[PDB]
Length: 330
Image (cartoon, rainbow, N blue to C red; front, side):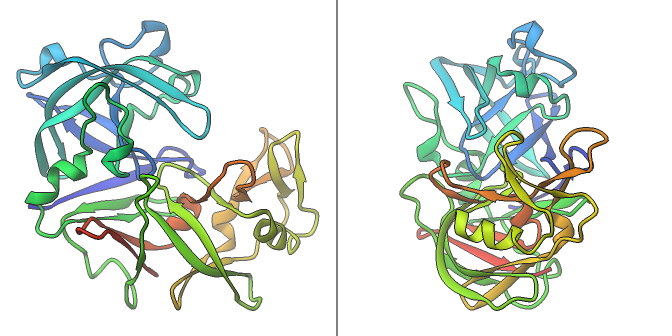
């Protein structure tokens, strides 16, 4: 089997991407944030504290003939941005782009933190990291990909995120028309539950490539590119007037600037992030100070190849017995 679904930016900045997901019988379609940095499929629901729902579409398990309460199971997750959610668990039928999993754990939110409430466009998350990170207790549950894997034509999914435009998540096949040149594959460590890999270095604009190992995670659920302070300083030093602002919470730059590109290495291959991808617009409405899309990972504890990086590539998440990651230009 295979599946193919379009993923769409939630706003004009590509702050996140939503993908429609069919849950239950008859189908209830919710728009979920596909997150290769976590491993829970959770949704706003009829059980979510009413004051914490503000415009989201909810899953109502009582209206699904295939929903079953997973007795005694609870979940609770906290994300890197400080947001969180928790609740109980149903199993139900879940389909993505024509690919169907029966008995998928659907984690129903009883509580969500304010940032979730405040974002009306995201109805929940669909985790695509390794199932070892799944938070369901006392019996850990599998991700949608893990459940679908054996049935897929090939044990892979691909992320093709757009810049200010829709893109595609495919399951079970590699669309050879979706990228240019070749796909370069690179080793993954699953030791921390992430799609963790090592970039071979970077360049700033038309500058020389610096060969240096950068360990980090391919994370579709993180907006920006978070890299070591040395690398980030080298980037922003090429932008007149750029500075790190503790009050804003990172590097800012004059909105009148033309940003240089940023290249990262995948083996001997190179992925080029155009400068425009690094502009996240005014820090506040009407400001001439703009927020940068490349930020320091210092104090995160891990480097994160988030959407800023991933949307410059066609990315293969290869879930073979020994997982690997593939990157192509597009």
